[PDB]
Image: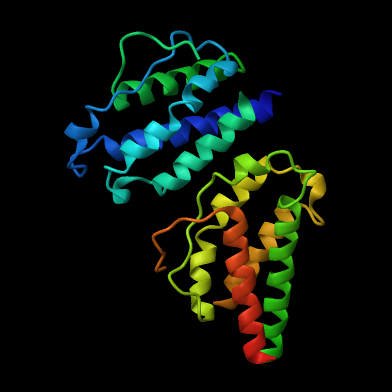
Length: 121
Length: 121
C-alpha cells in the first residue's frame, strides 16, 4: 500500500541514518574499535522479504552500539533499535562471503531502503 | 486539588490496566516477540515528579503496541497512549540497571498509581 509501506520504509531509513550519524564522528572515541566488529552482508537484497537479513544482524548491531556514546545519537540508541525491530517485523538469509564493517553494513541497508521507495514513487 | 489528582490518577491506572489486558491474552499471537523488547524502569517511583520516567518510555511503548492485535484492546491503543500522555503532562529520570519487559513495566507503574491513590484515599 504505497502509503503504509513507503511510510515505514522512510521511517526505517531515518532510524538507520540516525544510527550512522551517531557512531560516525569525532565525539565518538571508540569509532576505531567499533570498526573491527564483523557484520554479515546480504548477497541479494532486492525485496522486502530480504529484510530478514537485516533482522538477523540487529542483536550484533545492538551489542557493538554499546561501545558508542549515547549522547551523539539523536534518539536514544535503544529507541532506534526498537523502532527498526518493529518496522522489519511489520514489513518483511543468503549472506555474502566477505564480511563488512558497521559503516558499510548501515550504508548498504540505507541504500536498499532508498531503493524500494523509488519503486513506490 | 486532591480530588482532581485522585481523579487523574484513577484514570491513568485504568488506561494502564487496559493496555495490560490487550497485550496479556491468548488472542494476541505476537506476545512472545513483544516480550523481548526492553523497557527502562525507575530506580524509585515515590512521588508524582517521577512520572518523568514513564513519559520518557511512552514512545517505545506506543511502537511496540504496533505489534498487538488491536481488537483485543478495550479502547484504541492510540487513545490509551494519548490519555496517558495528557495525564502525565497534567500530573507531575534515575533509571535502574536490570531492564524489564512491557508486562513488568506496565505492572510497576500500575502499582505506583495504586500506591499514590492510597496516599490521598
